[PDB]
Image: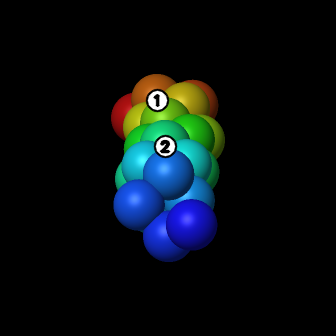
């Protein structure tokens, strides 16, 4: 099963983008 796993991977990358937004919010 790769289609369902790919859906989970897309969500994992989004979590990383959010962590980056919080880091930038603290710096600027």
Q: Secondary structure at mark 1?
A: helix
Do tag 2 and tag 1 residues touch (Cβ < 8 Å)?
no
Q: Residue at x 46, y 29 (%)?
A: 25
Q: Residue at x 41, y 61 (%)?
A: 3
Q: Residues within 10 Å of mark 2 (few under 14, many from 20)?
A: few
- Nearest to N terminus: mark 2 or mark 1: 2
- Label total for image: 2
As measured in the structure, the alpha-carbon distance from the residue carrying label 2 to the one carrying label 1 is 21 Å
Residue 27 visible to an observer of this rendering: no
Q: Is residue 16 above or below residue 26?
A: below
Q: Residues within 10 Å of mark 1 (few under 14, many from 20)?
A: few
Q: Which mark is residue 11?
A: 2
Tell me: 7 left or right of 23. Answer: left
Q: Position of residue 10 (x, y in %)?
A: 41, 53
Which residue does the numbered mark 1 point to in the structure image?
25
Q: Which mark is residue 3?
A: none
Front one among 17 and 13: 13
Front one among 8 and 24: 8
Nearest-to-viewer mark from 2 and 1: 2
Residue 28 visible to an observer of this rendering: yes
Q: Position of residue 24 (x, y in %)?
A: 46, 42
Q: Position of residue 6 (x, y in %)?
A: 45, 62
Q: Residue at x 57, y 66 (%)?
A: 1
Q: Is residue 2 above or below residue 8?
A: below
Q: Is residue 20 above or below residue 25?
A: below
């Amino acid at each position: 099963s790769d289609a369902a796993a790919r859906v989970t991977a897309i969500l994992s990358s989004l979590t990383v983008t959010q962590l980056l937004r919080r880091l930038h919010q603290w710096i600027s």
